[PDB]
Image 1: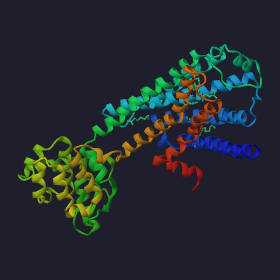
Image 2 (image 1 turned 90 degrees about the horizontal axis):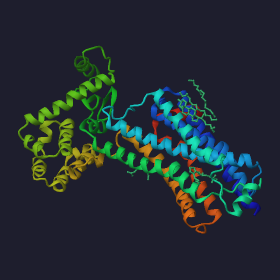
Image 3 (image 1 turned 120 degrees about the horizontal axis):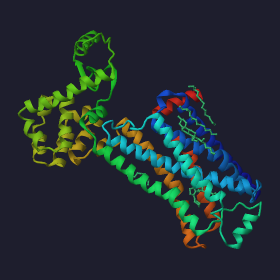
Image 4 (image 1 turned 180 degrees about the vertical axis):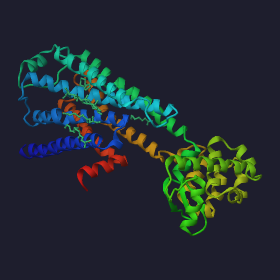
Length: 442
Ligand SMILES: CC(C)CCC[C@@H](C)[C@H]1CC[C@H]2[C@@H]3CC=C4C[C@@H](O)CC[C@]4(C)[C@H]3CC[C@]12C
Ligand SMILES: CC(C)(C)NC[C@H](O)COc1nsnc1N1CCOCC1
């Protein structure tokens, strides 16, 4: 139908436009802004490149093959088009597997969020991917090791107006296992460990950085008292110079109301140490700290950090039920407090920690932890976009008459739309957000 062709033509054009402009913007943002020239962003550059090659050389000719129902580019370009197509996908899934593995080695290292690979080393890994995956994508098609022995296929090979991808059962299993499933199985298992390590390796220092936050300039909290760094109270006095005086003495230099990351961490390491020391000095809190597990020990430290040894001691009724290990019971009395009303968002997180005995409340609450979530969304979406096509592709190998030709192309296109999703997912990263709007002048 006429309306169907024009209708599909517009949909496919807006898909192609979204692929190219999206990835160009991403590549441009990493190339221009220094703050985005990281090891993990260099892998994203390789991912965005493969996604750009898709919408520039693959997807455009794919559309013409559907709207005209015939190949009008020759048998040399037909095989080259298919070779690039496979490479784009193979390079993308291996890139995602590398990102996953590099994230495991970073989280297991004492660096926790910084990569063990250098900028020169990362370039080698990317170049090795494109070379290795380039060989497994071009050699099995150019040497015609992919060609089937049935008449319908040999007729399509000889025909210059036929580019229907016909294959033998061997290649269909071999190429799909090496190219897609092997990096996918590894990626899923390795990045599930990355998520498991992130949640498990959560500590009080990260927990307070989540709750209190970070600001290197003097600000007023909910209570209204002068604060700086990670919830470090300066004075209860409503005077800026009084707040500045107590600050310059603590650091030991002319700060002028501004501190560094090195300085903010230094006072934070002191406050945390003072909180625990205050618990050990307090007779009411001392036996409660003993009975609690590592996770709930941090939750008591968190309250002592915000209110103070004396303030936390006032919850006599609640503390008694923490010792009794009746978490759900203690939580109700903790909720029935002025502290709960003062900071409900922070109170919920701390109360839930006591209830669960896990960091489940502080799940992806950290900025470094949000970065991992975004990368997990990229890998997970690639799976949802490509796995249906790959399952049906291997189902076709076992039984020939299982699915129609229209089902194969439709599922292949589900994977094609994926090359337009990745730039929109980078909107989660505030570093990319600022880069994008700067290049778009908004
Ligand atoms: C279609 C085929 C033949 C062309 C393949 C394109 C090749 C040349 C491209 C695609 C991805 C590219 C890489 C993307 C990532 C980076 C990070 C950047 O900081 C330095 C260059 C480097 C390492 C690129 C080198 C060239 C590269 C490997
Ligand atoms: C069939 C067509 C139109 C050339 N698209 C190819 C697909 O987009 C993906 O191709 C692949 N990339 S990695 N492994 C594969 N496959 C899928 C098709 O069968 C051979 C192995």
